[PDB]
Length: 301
Ligand SMILES: CC(C)=CCC/C(C)=C/CSP(=O)(O)OP(=O)(O)O
Ligand SMILES: O=C1C(O)=CC(=O)c2c(O)cc(O)cc21
Ligand SMILES: [Mg+2]
Image (tube, rainbow, N blue to C red):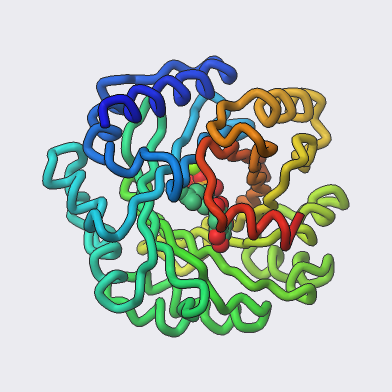
């Protein structure tokens, strides 16, 4: 429906406007049109995310895509929206759906850059482990090379994976995390092994509240690029930052970002990302939600 495309895009501009970011329609409209059938409210998920520091001048969007519509990356490449990297990443999404059960897909882009990634959701009652994932031919070798470490910290079940075709990186979204894993002692030990920024008390408190944790890996080396802790909540003041600027900006976004599910509070997903020399903050304000998010809020918020 051409109507849904316009509705979604307008909302995207609205979310971007709050951050002072302009949307490149030539890069966005073509993509929304291609997946116009998924933009229908009901069982669709759409998120508009902001980030601090370096990525403060950008705005990302995530749109769920049912598997019934077919491999999303095969679609964008075939439609000439994105060029094949020529690397294993081009086959990872196809191989994943070829080796494991995928319950849903998702496309991810940036308002000025365009399409950049896809997601592969697995059945909650049948999520793969690190072993099954590392077996995928096109999966980064780093996944297998970090299997022991993951097990040592209770990172086993993965609710989904994402592929960034531009940076050639893979995220593993671990789920069903144990309290032990999120303990301050466990978190510090983990970050130290990965050589990442050491979170302070505020950061540690956020980690403990996390419902999901995801490391980013690459095909070049076996070193994890970064690790992100995600918290889902209806609370608009959870940004784990001591910066007056972040406190104000994230709160503004969390209370004004567009959303269609009027009748309920805005679903928000905050992220604390730790990189080798620093940490930055993220916040996804959901424009479309489903029972999945509703269930997560009841369980972790
Ligand atoms: C349910 C849907 C459509 C997906 C939401 C997207 C999601 C889980 C956010 C992770 S992405 P992100 O936090 O931006 O981190 P990076 O790709 O930069 O590593
Ligand atoms: O945003 C969601 C989301 O909307 C639903 C999820 O199940 C999920 C997950 O398992 C892990 C994540 O890092 C994020 C999410
Ligand atoms: Mg993003």
